[PDB]
Image (cartoon, coloured by chain):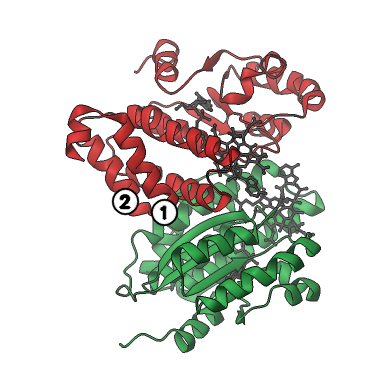
Chain colours: A green, B red
Amino acid sequence: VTASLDQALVARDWAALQARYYEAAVAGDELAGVALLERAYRSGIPVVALKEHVLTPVLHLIGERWRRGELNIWEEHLASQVTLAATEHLHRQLPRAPFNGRLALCGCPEGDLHEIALHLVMEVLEVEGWRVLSLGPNTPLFSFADAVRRFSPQLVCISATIVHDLERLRRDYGDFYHTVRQHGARIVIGGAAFADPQVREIFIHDYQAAGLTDFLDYLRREFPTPA
Amino acid sequence: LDQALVARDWAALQARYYEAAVAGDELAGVALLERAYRSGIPVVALKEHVLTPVLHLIGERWRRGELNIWEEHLASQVTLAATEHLHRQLPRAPFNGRLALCGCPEGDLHEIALHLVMEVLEVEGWRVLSLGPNTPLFSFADAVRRFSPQLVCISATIVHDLERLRRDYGDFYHTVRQHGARIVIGGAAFADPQVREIFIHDYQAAGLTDFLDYLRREFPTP
Ligand code: B12
Ligand code: B12
Ligand SMILES: C[C@H]1O[C@@H](n2cnc3c(N)ncnc32)[C@H](O)[C@@H]1O
Ligand SMILES: C[C@H]1O[C@@H](n2cnc3c(N)ncnc32)[C@H](O)[C@@H]1O
């Protein structure tokens, strides 16, 4: 009955894909979720475009609906678990560039619990042949700085959805930024928190990304690999 | 190393896991656990006598200033990733028709134990719906109305919102029973008698092993 899925894939009909991924996610259906993704990859849709044009829009909408009272916590929570599990499930299957000798250190700021974008980012990095160290969400800047001293990474990525602690962050940034520079590493930020110009001001950065596509453009210019 | 496996020298194994975890080295972490399993040690044993102790110690040392946040964060991601990786490489019982609904309470972010349990369930052939950590009690009930689970599992490490949970628990319990579900609780939060009192339950688990003993008595393998 359902080869109409396969017509959504061919047309690149993002809306229908979103709708079906949604139905799987809010229902806690890990397998239906991975299947939809798996099938769209082997149909030749790139992972990044799945991520930017199926997963991200769906989660935004889940949040818009939750806010308007059309959707409840339990449905987001299942969608969140499904998406974390399904993205990893797919990623373990993907081919990867050779190890590029480089180390990325990644996490989200203290008090922020939203970490799916972080996961999408770390995955992309691995596919490009980076070693990744995840501090995960809810990470103080001093903790970032400690880990930069310990590992001397080449890149620090921060995903930030929710930032309120402006004065603490203004204050810890100096030490963080100087540890980064002394180690010769670069800083890339993304996430909704940086729509606020005060937050963006604090988080002195080498590159602010809108999404994964332009992040990749940045990686290719800033950290090019031979062939 | 293979010496430590043969001897079953938990201490040596604990120490190597810790070294891998605080270094943020997922591959070494999985390697150790995988080698250990294939040297004859059940995964449950690895969970209880390697992962749990290493993580309780990370906490202790953090408290005493001997270990910093950055090192715990790394160990927690290593553990989440490592335990999932091993799980996917394990034999499972066939589906048993039964559904477990799993979560941690609202405002609690400690979620590794929940993963450890959910895994154990799937290996026993259960299907598992994960609400994840930081699940309001009413949000558990919402989900019991749908799905109609046979089991609800709750891991709790941090619980302080006593007056709310006290007043929300009535409806959640009603809903559980009128769907014939069972409630299993575990984790450090239930060492507090006021918390345990609110969380009317069918079994309280000390760890994973006795959890299995309870599942086999009450959910006899078809
Ligand atoms: C799922 C979710 C949660 C889950 C997350 C589970 C988890 N483990 O991650 C949980 C339950 C924790 C949660 C909690 C809350 N959240 Co919430 N929820 C979301 C939701 C629905 C989806 C988040 C998500 O995964 N987005 C997916 C990513 C991929 O989208 P994205 O962040 O836009 O990322 C893209 C780009 O920004 C970029 N990018 C992002 N980061 C980075 C980093 C780098 C380095 C680069 C290069 C690129 C990059 O690439 C991505 C793809 O192109 C959003 C809705 C939304 N708009 O996202 C809210 C939302 C962010 N949550 C919100 C709120 C209010 C809450 C709570 C305060 C609710 C409450 N308790 O009362 C709490 C706060 C907890 C905290 N302190 O962080 C609000 C925030 C609104 C606001 N800013 O005022 C939102 C917007 C929902 C809403 N519309 O109201 N939430
Ligand atoms: C990692 C960790 C964190 C991480 C969690 C990462 C993650 N995503 O899971 C983060 C950073 C989020 C964290 C934060 C905090 N936590 Co913390 N941290 C821990 C730590 C070190 C490990 C947790 C863990 O994975 N334990 C290992 C598990 C597998 O062991 P277990 O819970 O004993 O589970 C066993 C049994 O209980 C049973 N079980 C457990 N649950 C269930 C459920 C069911 C259904 C069943 C059948 C069985 C079962 O199975 C296991 C047997 O193998 C503990 C230390 C510790 N003692 O556990 C603290 C600890 C719990 N944290 C603590 C504190 C103080 C905090 C913070 C307040 C710190 C802060 N100021 O910010 C915050 C609070 C956040 C919150 N609201 O939840 C304290 C709590 C002390 C107390 N109760 O007062 C601890 C004990 C550390 C300490 N020594 O002081 N923490
Ligand atoms: C932004 C996301 O946060 C979740 N959310 C909203 N309020 C709570 C709460 N009290 N406890 C847990 N999660 C909550 C919703 O599911 C929403 O989609
Ligand atoms: C219980 C665990 O909580 C972590 N922890 C303690 N304080 C913070 C904080 N401000 N931000 C994030 N994690 C923290 C520590 O790593 C400890 O081991």
For the point 53% across and 23% down, which residue is it? B151
Quadrant location, the C terminus of chain A: bottom left
Q: Is residue A225 left or right of residue A69?
A: left
Ligand 2 has an atom within 8 Å of the beta carbon of the residue at disc 2: no
Say which amino acid is labelled 1.
Ala
Query: Answer yes or no: do the residues labelled 1 and 2 have beta carbons within 8 Å?
Result: yes
Q: Which mark is residue B28?
A: 2
Q: Where A80 falls versus B141 (above or below)?
A: below
Residue B112 seen by the camera: yes
Parent chain of label 1: B
Residue B17 percent coordinates (x, y)? 36, 42
Q: Crowding near pointer 1: few (<14 within 10 Å), some, many (20+)?
A: many
Does dot 1 land on a helix, a strand or a loop? helix
Say which amino acid is labelled 2.
Ala
Q: Nearer the viewer, mark 1 or mark 2?
A: 1
Parent chain of label 2: B
Does dot 2 land on a helix, a strand or a loop? helix
Q: Crowding near pointer 2: few (<14 within 10 Å), some, many (20+)?
A: some
Residue B174 percent coordinates (x, y)? 71, 17
- What is the quadrant of residue A137 in the picture? bottom right
Residue B94 seen by the camera: no
Residue matched to label 1 = B23
Q: Is residue B160 left or right of residue B55?
A: right
Picture mark count: 2
- Frontmost residue, B176 versus B154: B154
